Length: 38
Image 1 (cartoon, helix red, strand yellow):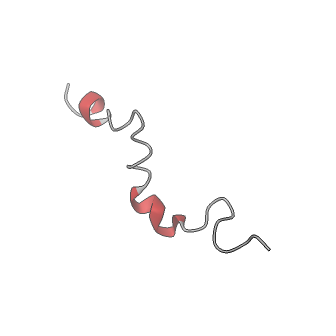
Image 2: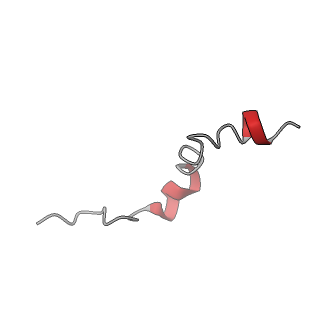
């Protein structure tokens, strides 16, 4: 059976702690080079 630990938000308890940077950076890593200067 397929159900180890990835439903849709398995361990986002911590992924989210820094994947979202490393994700919401697809173009929010521009947030920096885009939303953090001017």
